Length: 162
Ligand SMILES: [Cl-]
Ligand SMILES: [Cl-]
Image 1: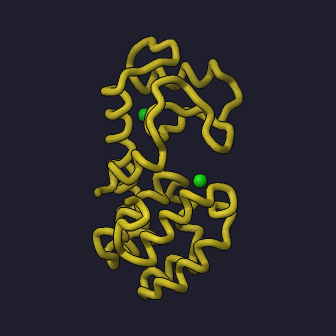
Image 2 (image 1 turned 180 degrees about the vertical axis):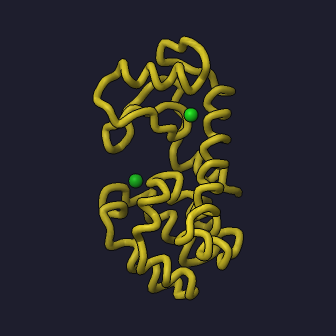
């Protein structure tokens, strides 16, 4: 198991524009297109992202390409972030993947806002961090996926994904 396989299980793969759990236009493997309510604004962002007139549909290769960019960006965002970087550096490989997953999902700013949780992770207080992580809109809105990430943080294993 690795970050790619982990996020692919969590996000799934869709080749046609779809709406995410928040109702936003997305495509491929959790690639957010726009928060705008316009489907046209979504196709536009899509064509721009892919470099061709897609008419809202992409191929598997194209999906995987956006995915690779998105993972790469998540990692680089963590490393550039003063709040996130020290947490990431402190963790083991498995838990690093959990942090990347959260960043992929809610963006760097979102994650950096989990001040108390971050401190607990840095301190290696696993059970405590897991409890604090659950007291969030994140957990309440997407509980099954949040539990998988939380368990990963708590245990340091891939059990939740197997
Ligand atoms: Cl892009
Ligand atoms: Cl869920």
